[PDB]
Image 1 (tube, rainbow, N blue to C red):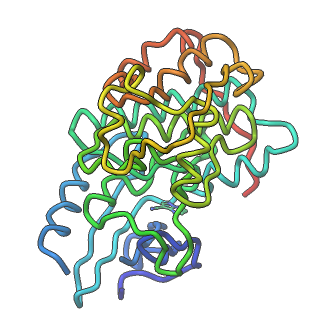
Image 2: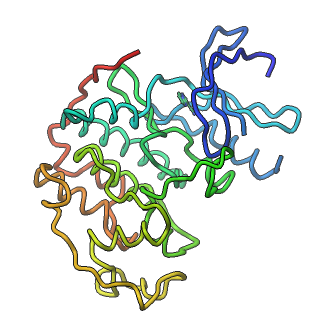
Length: 290
Ligand SMILES: N#Cc1cnn2cccnc12
């Protein structure tokens, strides 16, 4: 693209290469995404108007030469590297709470417009020096489906995937995003992924092992989902105090609601913003290494 000067490759999404680049007329540095169906162009252009302080701004959509490029605001780090970087000591809780609170704000906005992310994970949560956290690639899954490999044949992570998706539900809701964000929340607290599955059954069975094999008591209609099998092992549910120590009562309460099996029982973003866990939320600034 002639108006852009590629500074460096900085990623490789499900969708393709991500470059840091600098607008040749506007001086602007941006994230340049290389990704043509009529539908997909009409879906992306909706995304241009879906603006929020906790959503990485889509600056431009360039359709030229049957190539598609998306230009986003550039942020210098993602939550994955920040988490690796804070492995030895952990993210201080007040910072974890701030990030969760901002991310729920993002989702509450998106969801109010009936837009899902579908593929939340630490690598798509982008952090700045100001104590801000933003959701990247929002709305991209519906525009281009969610691949098993990346264009680089990289394996797409299952770790944050909701059970109803794993169980073959076609028509899933905004609750899928709540699940993922609860998995990330647990991960920030404990410094280990909650459910690090390396296939779909392994991901489903890691879920069942911590939370209990769902049944018709806790999840009405589960046994009639497309990929449910009566032969599932029946595992007992673990208590959360074992799952996420040393998270406090409020956090653990909030966490369990974000991880309800039944997508209709699972906490909404808007209702999670009201949880008393956030009573004393503040906005710390992280110490970063640019
Ligand atoms: N999409 C996107 C995006 C915006 N800023 N970024 C920095 C690093 C990696 N990806 C991005």
